Image (cartoon, coloured by chain):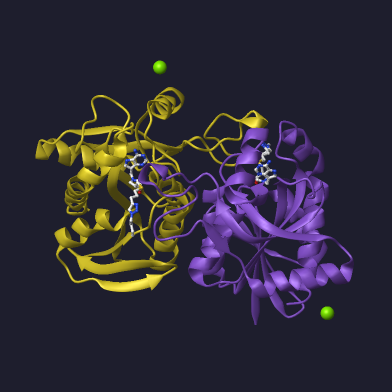
Chain colours: A purple, B yellow
Amino acid sequence: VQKIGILGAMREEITPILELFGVDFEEIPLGGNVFHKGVYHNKEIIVAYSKIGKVHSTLTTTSMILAFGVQKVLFSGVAGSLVKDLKINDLLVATQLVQHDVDLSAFDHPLGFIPESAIFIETSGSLNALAKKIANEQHIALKEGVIASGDQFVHSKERKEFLVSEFKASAVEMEGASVAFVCQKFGVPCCVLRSISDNADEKAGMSFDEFLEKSAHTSAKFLKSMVDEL
Amino acid sequence: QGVQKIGILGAMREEITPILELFGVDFEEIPLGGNVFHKGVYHNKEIIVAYSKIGKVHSTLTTTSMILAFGVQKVLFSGVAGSLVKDLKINDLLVATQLVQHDVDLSAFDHPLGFIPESAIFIETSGSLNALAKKIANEQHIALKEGVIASGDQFVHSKERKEFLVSEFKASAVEMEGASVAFVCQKFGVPCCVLRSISDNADEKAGMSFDEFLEKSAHTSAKFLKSMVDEL
Ligand SMILES: CCCCn1cc(CCCSC[C@H]2CN(Cc3c[nH]c4c(N)ncnc34)C[C@@H]2O)nn1
Ligand SMILES: CCCCn1cc(CCCSC[C@H]2CN(Cc3c[nH]c4c(N)ncnc34)C[C@@H]2O)nn1
Ligand SMILES: [Mg+2]
Ligand SMILES: [Mg+2]
């Protein structure tokens, strides 16, 4: 049987996932998370929100893999746009991810780099190819690019522009890199999907509060369409 | 259950080398999630030793693996740290009373720095283990300080950042893993003790000081950690 892990960061990012799948879920508490376990089209689906940020998302992804035996992990949620062509509600699939707030420059390491790791973490080529194929079939724009993750909500021109100049990132969030990193360490295929909620600038807090629901639903609907192909 | 299982963590290989040597028992090496776990028996206790690799994500992963895959009932962390206070000198030992993720910033939503919804700024460690540390330090006639440790994904090497950590969090030392290790332990209800020996002063010379004192400071912490395990 296929076991698929489905993650968001916030409750609001998984509410539409649970609703759209429309099946009965058993709630299983572990490590401060609640995992929603159900069956959908001959697949076991395990849905959870990690809570915000890198430590939360690292923990939850590790629990999904070790405790629930998931064979793939699909992340769905919202993100800040760093580029003019990614508008509110647009979908992005992460090709690579970086931890943008990592700084070991005192030892002459590039920003984002940790010894025994890499700046950029890869996601699954096969899953990203699937996303692109289905987006083309649905006539929805799906961009691909680098996502930057850190433990700060970005809401300034200065920081946005650093993420673009340093990492060539297209979007910013607080969990993708950690989720993809854990999946890489365990050899588990990972796809990170995000819908834009804000422009990561001085108005981002207000934009985020306004568009979280709609953008979360947009990502959730696309994630469901991916699970339908697995 | 019926057997005691103790997880022992460092961040870097250099922090666990003296731990493995000092325990002096045979370890089985078990690979999982990009870590190697060293599993042995010591004084009727199962000990599982690993280095996580540097920073918050690495240490979160490894601690979660220790708990879920190896069933550890306690986690003891040993390693080095930057001093933020004049009375913590190179080689001095500190036990963390509470820890904070100093680089967390959700201030755009009016949250205090360090705070994430559904969590807390300060993460507590085990009172019983910290009390044990203080008791044995007094017996050994070694100075053991206690205080707040700040953890983030930056090596701190500036006056400006040091002073922020003191003013914002009243931190005594800085490192890149303690808060994440303690956080994971809290989520799983596992007692945690974080021990650090000072390697540098988290200032403009910290890189050079760290390279000089990593080995000695790591050994100082490892030796103290072993003395704790001897009392469990
Ligand atoms: C949850 C408790 C209820 C009260 N409450 C809600 C909140 C909201 C905290 C949201 S932190 C951000 C989320 C969204 N998410 C993506 C994101 C979108 N835009 C971003 C940006 N500009 N910078 C960084 N990340 C983002 C990151 C984090 O999970 N604070 N208190
Ligand atoms: C396997 C190849 C390793 C090659 N290599 C080693 C290195 C050194 C990286 C060291 S990062 C720092 C370690 C030590 N440790 C504690 C620490 C002590 N002082 C601190 C300070 N001032 N600020 C923050 N943290 C510290 C954090 C991290 O594990 N770079 N390349
Ligand atoms: Mg088809
Ligand atoms: Mg001052």
Q: As drawn, is B133 to the left or to the right of A45?
A: left
In this view, which residue lies farthest toward the bottom? A1
Q: Can residue B115 be seen in this view?
A: yes
Residue B30 lies, with reference to residue B204, above or below; the image says: below
Residue B20, how many percent across, how many down?
A: 20, 62
Residue B175, how many percent across, how many down?
A: 36, 41
Residue A148, how many percent across, how many down?
A: 61, 50
- Quadrant of residue A98 in the image? bottom right
Q: Is residue B197 visible?
A: no
Ligand number 3: quarter of image = bottom right
Tell which of B40 and A137 is nearer to you: A137
Residue drawn at x 40%, y 61% as measured from the top left: A116
Q: As drawn, is A3 to the left or to the right of B174?
A: right
Tell which of A189 and A23 is nearer to you: A189
Residue drawn at x 17%, y 54% as measured from the top left: B230
Residue drawn at x 10%, y 35% as measured from the top left: B141
Residue A28, how many percent across, how many down?
A: 61, 62
The N terminus of chain B - image quarter: bottom left
Tell which of A9 and B67 is nearer to you: A9
Residue B205 lies, with reference to residue A219, above or below; the image says: above
Q: As drawn, is B232 to the left or to the right of B52?
A: left
Residue B222 lies, with reference to residue A116, above or below; the image says: above
- Quadrant of residue A33 in the image? bottom right
- How many marks overall? 0
